Image (cartoon, coloured by chain):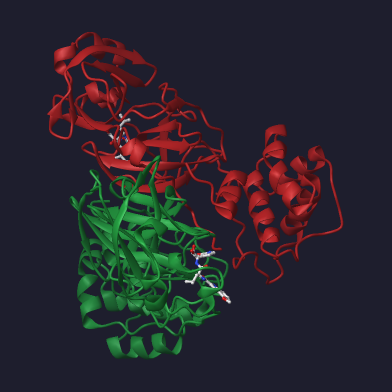
Chain colours: A green, B red
Amino acid sequence: SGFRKMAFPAGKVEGCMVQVTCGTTTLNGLWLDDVVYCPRHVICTSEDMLNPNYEDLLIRKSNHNFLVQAGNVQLRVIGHSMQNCVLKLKVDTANPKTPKYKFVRIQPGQTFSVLACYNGSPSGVYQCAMRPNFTIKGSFLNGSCGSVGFNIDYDCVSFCYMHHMELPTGVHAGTDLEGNFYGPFVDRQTAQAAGTDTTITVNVLAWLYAAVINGDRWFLNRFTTTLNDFNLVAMKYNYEPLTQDHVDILGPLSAQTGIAVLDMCASLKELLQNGMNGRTILGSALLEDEFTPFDVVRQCSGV
Amino acid sequence: SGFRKMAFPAGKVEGCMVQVTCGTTTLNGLWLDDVVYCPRHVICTSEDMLNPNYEDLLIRKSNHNFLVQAGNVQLRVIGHSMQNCVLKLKVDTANPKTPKYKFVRIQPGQTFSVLACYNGSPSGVYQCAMRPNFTIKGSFLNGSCGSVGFNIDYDCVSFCYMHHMELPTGVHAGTDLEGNFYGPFVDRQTAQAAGTDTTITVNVLAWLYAAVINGDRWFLNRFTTTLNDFNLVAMKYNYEPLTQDHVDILGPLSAQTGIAVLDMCASLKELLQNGMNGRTILGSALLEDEFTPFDVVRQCSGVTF
Ligand SMILES: *[C@@](O)(CO)[C@H](C[C@@H]1CCNC1=O)NC(=O)[C@H](CC(C)C)NC(=O)c1cc2c(OC)cccc2[nH]1
Ligand SMILES: *[C@@](O)(CO)[C@H](C[C@@H]1CCNC1=O)NC(=O)[C@H](CC(C)C)NC(=O)c1cc2c(OC)cccc2[nH]1
């Protein structure tokens, strides 16, 4: 029993983190085979970062301009190219710790594990969710650029995130491993805002099922709602609409607890309209929305 | 910026997790150098666990009764001994991935990363706080016994926890790496209840220092207090009393902010006696008590290992 924000074991990724320095700029890189991936703004100086013409800045660079260190050993750069906001630094040595990996673009509402690194050295691991406005609520300080987010399926690491920026509001933004930002963000040194931060409804419902599986039911009620009437109320509160696909994804949690999805929706509607008073759900005073249905199934199946 | 429950990178521990099996009973063990550590109840059958005599049950076992596997590779057991509730098995191979490590016994309020493991395979990592009642609010399923909790310092992994038990309330109990349980629990198949829990005062204060570091300081008041007077008051609100070590580990955050420890105790005292008055701290109206001073420091300054 029990339910906790849980990340994947990061050992397979820890063996891929390196340090990338260009001039006075340093951040993290991801070393897979004989390629090191890192945010392209490492080639920038403090002045270039205000408005960088990356294609212009990149052509004026040589291989020896890039200092790549894997722990103690320094890796010799024998080529370099750009794929959107990701610099690809070819090296004369293939990482012997390269695991089975793939590059994927995660969907909003989905979760992944982040391996926060500084100076190429892992520092901490935690789980994040790709929010509807394509930001993530992480913990990133100066020098965390180049940190990656990932999921693991058996023996395959699916890389989905590389960190680039912290918005003025304190949330964070980044790209997939092909260098495409999540959201309307750009890698220039400017204050940038995201779209309205809507709540991942299917995740909140999954988290309510987890609370019930762990013996908490004070928020349940005998009322019921139609899918449309629930979505009417949810959208009023800046919640994402619940699709029939979401209803289907919640099936296992419904079968395990015996609470129909539309029954849980009636509970959430009451919570949204009445609040939680001073009560808590799984120790939280707010409705948690960064647990996916699968995150709940993996921790609550058989409980 | 940002504040999260953050676990340590677990690569150094993942390379040490193995599976230990006796008969049909299987759990996790910790492979360090040429010794594997694991809960002693692996030697029990399902019925043995109801009322085991581990000394008697162990006398009937030999080295050849122990199946130790790293993945699918068997590690031949060449020696066995019992230390409290932990079984120590000498194997013929020294773990090449053994990291710098030490065995430590933590205090209530200290946090550590748990590497949840099943059949010797790491499955998840999350941060836990040792409650004052010597339980942890973990997430453990069948086959999780032998999972360890740890901290990482000078490239050294300090092992502090090995999983054994789930309580009826849904919390969890275990031992240190010397087999000594945290709290008054025993490795037996019975429903055992933990004492009444309390809030970890030192961690709440650390969380208040965190808010002040971030410019959120409305709660800072003009009063101070003695350590003794605060402890007597805090206990009336189900808060644990502070020790001299607690005051000392709060030192760095006290110097960083310029707020004396006993001054912030007086501020917390007012929050307990008067409430928040519809206000929040770091975005929450709930006082957080599972962030140690180091966690606040390690996360407000990005220390690596
Ligand atoms: C990377 O480590 C840079 O190498 C760093 C990310 C963080 C810094 C602190 N916490 C983090 O997560 N990223 C940046 O500094 C980026 C660099 C861009 C992509 C070139 N810049 C920002 O994240 C950024 C800039 C500004 C800004 O300007 C002016 C105004 C307000 C917020 C802001 N964030
Ligand atoms: C280990 O994996 C066993 O090897 C397992 C712990 C969990 C199983 C699911 N989630 C967990 O955390 N541990 C046990 O099953 C222990 C075995 C002891 C140490 C011999 N037993 C319990 O945790 C336990 C027993 C009982 C009980 O009796 C019957 C009544 C109520 C609760 C309870 N928990």
> Residue B153 at x, y = what percent?
50, 36
Which residue appears at 33% of the width and 62% of the height? A112
Which residue appears at 47% of the width and 39% of the height? B135
Residue B166 quadrant: top left
> Residue B276 at x, y = what percent?
70, 65
Residues A79 and A37: in front is: A79
> Residue A73 at x, y = what percent?
37, 41
Q: How many marks?
A: 0
Residues B222 and B239: in front is: B222
Residues B254 and B130: in front is: B254
Quarter occupied by the N terminus of chain B: bottom right
Q: Is residue B149 above or below residue A62?
A: above
> Residue B29 at x, y = what percent?
28, 29
Q: Is residue A117 above or below residue A253?
A: above
Q: Quadrant of ligand 2?
A: top left
Residue B119 in the figure: left or right of residue B52: left
Q: Is residue B158 above or below residue B77?
A: below
Residues A193 and B141: in front is: A193
The answer to whether residue A209 of the structure is visible from this angle is no
The answer to whether residue A60 of the structure is visible from this angle is yes
Residue B304 in the figure: left or right of residue B253: left
Residue B27 in the figure: left or right of residue B67: right
